[PDB]
Image (tube, coloured by chain):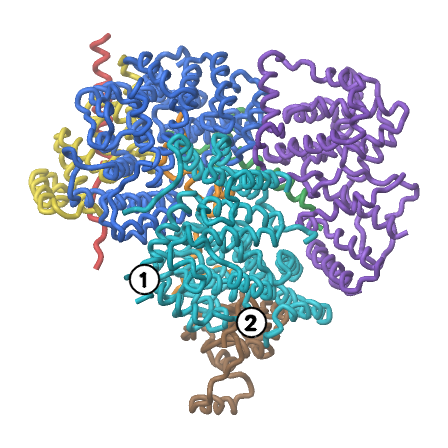
Chain colours: A purple, B orange, C blue, D cyan, E green, F brown, G yellow, H red
Amino acid sequence: KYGPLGITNFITPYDLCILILIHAHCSQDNGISVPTAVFLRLISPTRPSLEWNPLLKDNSNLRSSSIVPPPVLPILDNIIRILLDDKDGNKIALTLMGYLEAINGLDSINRLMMDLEKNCLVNNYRSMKMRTTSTRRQMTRASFLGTFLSTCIRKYQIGDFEMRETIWINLQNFKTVFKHTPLWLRFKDNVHIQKVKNCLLANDEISVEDQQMVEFFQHFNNGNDADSKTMNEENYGTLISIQHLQSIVNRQIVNWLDYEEQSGLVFDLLDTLSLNDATKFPLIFILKYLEAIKENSYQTALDSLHNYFDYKSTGNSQNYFHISLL
Amino acid sequence: SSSSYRDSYFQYRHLPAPHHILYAEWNQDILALPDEVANITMAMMTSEQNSN
Amino acid sequence: QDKIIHDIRIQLRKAATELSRWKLYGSSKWAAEALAGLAPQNGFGLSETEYDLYLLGSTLFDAKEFDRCVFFLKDVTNPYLKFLKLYSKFLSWDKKSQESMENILTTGKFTESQSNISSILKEINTFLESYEIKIDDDEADLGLALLYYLRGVILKQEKNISKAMSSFLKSLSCYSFNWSCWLELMDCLQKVDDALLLNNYLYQNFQFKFSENLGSQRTIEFNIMIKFFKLKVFEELNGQLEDYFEDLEFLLQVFPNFTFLKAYNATISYNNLDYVTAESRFDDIVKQDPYRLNDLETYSNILYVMQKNSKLAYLAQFVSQIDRFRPETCCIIANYYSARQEHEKSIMYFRRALTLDKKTTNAWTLMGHEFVELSNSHAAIECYRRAVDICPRDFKAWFGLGQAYALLDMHLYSLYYFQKACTLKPWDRRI
Amino acid sequence: DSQDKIIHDIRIQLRKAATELSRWKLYGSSKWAAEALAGLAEAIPQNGFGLSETEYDLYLLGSTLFDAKEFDRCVFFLKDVTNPYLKFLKLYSKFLSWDKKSQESMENILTTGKFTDQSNISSILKEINTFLESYEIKIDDDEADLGLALLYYLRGVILKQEKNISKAMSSFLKSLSCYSFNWSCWLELMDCLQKVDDALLLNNYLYQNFQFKFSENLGSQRTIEFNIMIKFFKLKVFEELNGQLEDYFEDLEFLLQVFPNFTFLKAYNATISYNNLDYVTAESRFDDIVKQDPYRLNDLETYSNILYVMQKNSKLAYLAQFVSQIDRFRPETCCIIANYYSARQEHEKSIMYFRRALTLDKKTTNAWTLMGHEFVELSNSHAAIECYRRAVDICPRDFKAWFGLGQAYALLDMHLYSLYYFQKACTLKPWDRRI
Amino acid sequence: KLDEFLMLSEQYKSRLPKIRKLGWNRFKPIGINKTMYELEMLRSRARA
Amino acid sequence: VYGDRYIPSRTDIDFNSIVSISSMVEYQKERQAHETYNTLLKNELFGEMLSKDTVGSESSIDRIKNTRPEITRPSSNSVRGASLLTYQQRKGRRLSAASLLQSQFFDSMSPVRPDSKQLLLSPGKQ
Amino acid sequence: MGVMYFKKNEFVKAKKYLKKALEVVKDLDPSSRTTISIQLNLGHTYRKLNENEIAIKCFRCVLEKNDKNSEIHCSLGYLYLKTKKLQKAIDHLHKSLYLKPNNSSATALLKNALELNVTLSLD
Amino acid sequence: MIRRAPTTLQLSHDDVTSLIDDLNEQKLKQQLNIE
């Protein structure tokens, strides 16, 4: 599940996973309602901004009155293990599994995005009661999921084609990573995928001629390894936004300061930053600073401390020199 | 058809990096002329006086 | 066939190497590609003290340091090394020779002029007049043809088309088997009745220099790409065809699995508005040469009419995967956005594709259509105008102006614009 | 006597050296090879390749599709070829397809590197190793052709980009032994060097246990003492790393005799005076370059650097207008103008060009410190701190970046907080009065 | 701290109508000596 | 004698000092009277940084007037103005010559800087 | 002098002196506002003299010498409108208004060409 | 010493308007013959 890590201001493959589930919940054709606990664990880390001063203030507001589960890494192995736990969660998990097999192209991704904006998302509740002829559940902008989906929709129209192209390379790279895992072998065939996949694959408008070359366009791009692959630039294994990464690091340092976490996965992934994510995300430096104190390293701790206060000072419009010295 | 077979003008392969077209606006920048336009910085009829 | 095909191989090997030697990428790319489709002879007039300059001039050109090449060859008395300096001098001017009005549209920034080529043209005339051996008689060689070809294209810049034909035909007589020279000959026609008049010139008045060429190639009718000339003219403008079907068959038997012929052959189906047969012919090319990107925007254009967005989206994904900054890649992507009714964003990618060649196929016209759906009606009419200036043989460019002016209250302008396009394509029922 | 015989030898070799390197469509050394021949002191074409007429047709398709920027299409047609001359071309096409492709992928990314300081790349590396074992020479033999030597160059450069140093060094030495006079090969070799003590270890290896293939190279050249690339290595690494000089004086005057009109030598000679804070003599040396070679956007970045200190604003204003007229896409031409715009106390505009000059080529890390200075004169200390800090994160061994970052804190009242930055800069260049 | 996503959202929103707004003001066709800005101005007065 | 570009020397003038320096019918006469007093005050009170700076000719008053944020002849055309860091300035002094002792002499009777005296002695426009 | 004698509507000594000037400077001054000016003036005298035939050729040769010029295109369009060659004059007019924005006289002449195109019914 | 642009004159308004009027005459009189 490991891979190079990079901050992305676009639709991460993790973001579509929530978009997959919310489509199933709102469509109400299958009668599967995603448990409220599953949602509050997935969208909530993506919610913007927590902030954390290095020192001089400890857990003033970061502590939650109710204990919260750890944020979820953007790997299909970790996401599935949440839904899989329920006795009926296989039905919920396979719904996510089925959709990820149905979306075989970039146009299919646009189909899901187009579907939600036109029908599911609703500007205000005053138009809700007039839309009693809708066969699918509708959502308000101000709701918990409504404000999230608006940002996700905004993050799709904010990009050119090169943006949409990176979505589909990484998702298949993200999807094929889960394929080479023992968990996939246990679910190699469950026949619920085939039923749900054919539910959305219908109305393809062609099955005899174009589908022969549709496979060719997909297969040639993919690494069939029959010949030398088409050469392309190195692509990141995992894509995370700034806000989601903030939730992972804030939870990690708080847990370090004083449902099982994955210390090995988080630490390994954070060590593969392209040195420009570290500038956009200064807190990686202090994560080394806390570790350096644990082993009582003098020179190593100071360098990481100075690094954190050079990037943070420039990012903060407010003067932070008087905080760096303390 | 036939597009890249003609070489009678500046094309996408004559410049070294094909991705320089992404910027493609630096050509239309008038460079500040040497002496008089130094006064417009101070001001931010007067520029010609500083040229004099 | 028999020895005729063997005689083509040896001489076509020449046109692939010498043309590539003197920095003519476009012509050599066609000739080299023709070797693969077809089922080290070295020699040049140079001295040791002058051979170094060619190595010096060639390697600086390859590093794309155009201007420094001109200085280092300030004096060169070699018959045809002078061409390399003059070629670099021409392109160094061209990259900064962007018309002010056209530039606003192609960029959107919204913010010595031509006397160089006047000196460039005068230099070529001065050098030729003082050169030892002229074009007449069995004199001259490959090198002089490049000088005349370069002289012809500069002449076309000032729209001296009448004298441009004489220069190009004179270059082809000296040296044949140069594809890039004939492409510039296409743009000189801009009419239908002159093509047969030019065809009459080739059949009677024109003659080849047998000294440079190999056997069975001085004769016009045994030549192989005089058929290529006839193939190109009768697809750009139909008119009245002479031996068009018969010579096409002979060129198909030769050059097996040649991708350019198949793309040309299938483009005929698009010109005949037979879309169902066009896709099948286009698809076979994709299987054979997946990494060939030339004339792929026609494939997107055909798919646009059929509105097979699912098939079209994968084509854009496949095309953009292997290359993201060639003119056909951006043109296809820009065509994709139109299918999604995002006419406001298709301009951006059409804009990017234009800045790559600025003399493309009908990418100017497709830019104009996207403005019309935005009801701008003023960018489109001027965007349509630029396509007229570059290629006055484009039916869609003229029609867009007449169609756009029809919406405008003054319909009297639209009569003239429709009249010109009427002569170009009288067969259309709509016009 | 013997010197004239050497001159006649160099011309034959440099005519040969620029031939195949340009013929094999790599311009790192081809451009430099012709430059050396042009500046050589005044005192039938040569070509040969073991290719069959059947496979030679593929070369024309491969070579012409290369410079037409369609690298990927060249790979598909040249897949099944087995000749080592062509096998290098296919993998060179694949590598440049990736190297080009990576450039378009990141343009908003200014800083380059990994914070802690492949799979697609490893595909090329495996093909090199698989082909190398199958072929029936595998170096270390007298009958070693140019292509196998040239093939090792690709193996070295592809290894370095994976950060597998100390194995690319050995590969370059094997390629260099079989074929010298490959300037681009030397530069990659120079890059992997990091400290002066490494150069002394590398310099010794070139002397005791290093010998060239006398079969491939022409006579009276394979000798290490009379070579030219070994000399050019001495002037390059010994001074760019500012290392202790040895066997450097007698070589420099030897090169000036053989190469009196070489543009690269004089500019390097001018840079030596520049590096020693001797600006007046540096100006005279550079003035010969502009008159002799007016179009050279390679070392003018120091020329426009000298003029800023000289306060010759008129002369600099000439250069900004003249340099910008050639082209505005080179890294240097966007650095020449920025100096001119900085001298006129217009910082909000000069700051723009320095970011521009860096975007075109991210290897030019010298522009980070200059970009930092224009913020301090703008009374914007917060922005400057990040600008300096990126420079040291690209390469920690940057005396300019540490000092420029130390001052920005010293300008503020935070005197002690700047002591650490100055202390770090001390270890880089202890032998400096300024620090 | 300036949100890089938020600032890049306003940048896209600003440049989007700018393509549509191209023909306004300076742009003038041949045979019409008046630009399209006041074509809609007189059109507005026509109904009103 | 010429400072390096990459390692500039720092002048004594501080960040906020330039913020101070750059700060700006009988009403017109009073406004003109106030402006010359303010310019003279900031010229005299400052200028130690400006005296250490500069290379030749010119004046500290010209440097202050050049800071962006009947006329007599201007000496030199440099418009550098105030600056935190200087490159050209490396500490160097000209040898004493008879003009210098003439200059230090007309300065002996002056309680203020010669440049300020020239500014005040300059006639305002009537 | 040729301009001077054109102003007083003599149109004979003007032509003679301008032709003499042109034969004097046949060899030199191929460009640079001297050959262009003299040939344009001579063509204008021929146009006012109603000898439009040679005027066509001289205006054409000036146009091929230098092309970015609104005056040459407007005068050539006027010459064509003097005869009946509207198909070959409307393009020149359109190019002239492309080159220079206003060209009020050119606009009026082009508008008249439009009404002619309406009136005519050629196949 | 520098020479300015030599005096050149173009189509005035009076002659072009006269040609307009004559052109109207000839596109006005011929349809009377047709009718």
Q: Position of residue D277 (x, y in %)?
A: 50, 72
Q: Nearer the viewer, residue F36 or F45?
A: F45
Q: Is residue G92 left or right of residue A153?
A: left
Q: Which mark is residue F35?
A: 2
Q: Secondary structure at mark 1?
A: helix
Q: Is residue D344 left or right of residue C70?
A: right
Residue at point 46%, 44% (across, down): D147
Q: Position of residue A4 (x, y in %)?
A: 69, 42
Q: Nearer the viewer, residue D305 or D36?
A: D36
Please, which chain is the residue tagged with disc 1 on?
D
Eyeballing the image, is D396 above or below C149? below
Q: Which mark is residue D5?
A: 1
Q: Which mark is residue A111?
A: none
How many other residues sit within 10 Å of disc 1, few (<14), some (14-19) or many (≥20)?
Answer: few
Eyeballing the image, is F91 above or below C114? below
Can residue D209 be seen by looking at this rendering?
A: yes
How many other residues sit within 10 Å of disc 2, few (<14), some (14-19) or many (≥20)?
Answer: few
Residue at point 53%, 67% (across, down): F5
